[PDB]
Length: 447
Ligand SMILES: O=c1ccn([C@@H]2O[C@H](COP(=O)(O)OP(=O)(O)O)[C@@H](O)[C@H]2O)c(=O)[nH]1
Image 1 (tube, rainbow, N blue to C red):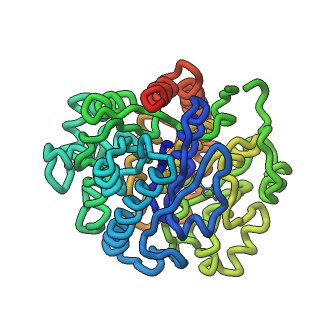
Image 2 (image 1 turned 90 degrees about the vertical axis):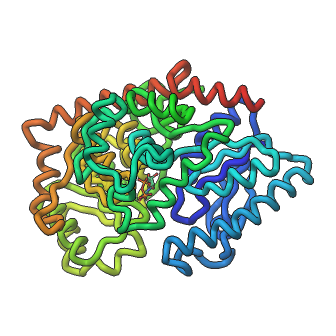
Image 3 (image 1 turned 180 degrees about the vertical axis):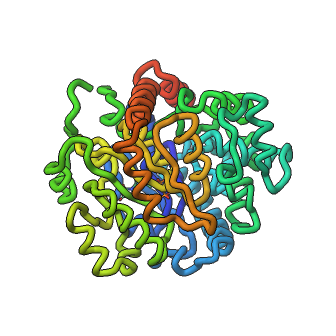
């Protein structure tokens, strides 16, 4: 089979690799999703065409990340148990008459490539972040840039035609520009690339037209092939596609609420599945939303919602809806959706692009500051919130950015760019498109 090993944490996102796997199954390959025992027992399996299998991260009954909140210690524990149990899985698969043909893995777990290579299984790295960020990490790994990475280093790469934007201090990836703040994440980011040259294939969830210089450099430097955006075929208009109302229509109550709002009127608001906001930050964000006067759909996770006051929740009742989780793709495809106030995680960004939704970017760390710069400066599909002198986001700034995207003199600029990139994203994944071609090549290689 083809084994698919997304980053084996509950906080990891399996769907981009599953959508790659669905495309491989269309070409006749047989995919298995490999997750932790904890994830397997706490989420529904993917269903046809997938098998499921498990490894362990040390914690089969509880969440390893809650147990081990120091990131370095969680990652060392995952490596020790994961590598052992992955080896055991490769053997048990072979003994069950399903020897793995290839292991597709997120190199944010680079021990997986060692284990598979030692089992004589081909390996394909699946980069889950944008080429722009990936190449900066790769230059550090390759010892072409020292730590910390500076805006001067970034300006060099722009000048050499590698980066298509000039990154300032608030735009360079903090895990390498401020590595003392997050030692384990700095190491994780760089070690993604350590030994990547030994893989059979290297894949990235992006498309060439979005980041042309960066994807070209990733291809020539790391053999990376673009295979995205790795989203459901429906949202890419890929029939293997006529008039636009979502045929993949759920019963989720927030969708009923969106159905009653006017076209392009609603602000979707999410800071993703990992970041935590303190009470003060939630208060500035929620008041900004209320102060905007727009309808809004605010995702506040179950594990965060204790921080919302009664009074702010009531204020949000006037025009807003607060939910713990939404069907974000379905939301973004909805005719009522006008803009997305996002932390600019890459999956959320790609989902916004495929649906032509303009962005208000509120980045925290990882790839988000970089993505937010591309959003505002190269892609032109939205604006980034400006923090005050002490690094605080103020309610007045939240409000001003919402208004600027929905009502400002440049409203039509952001919409125009979003629509333009939407069309190119779809093209890339349709038959004969730049990403589709790389998927087909891979599939033939492993048939
Ligand atoms: O209410 C929500 C919040 C998030 N997501 C999905 O969760 C992923 C979040 O990934 P992202 O890279 O944006 O950031 P993270 O959450 O890892 O910071 C995306 O696929 C979202 O569509 C969702 O479906 N519903």
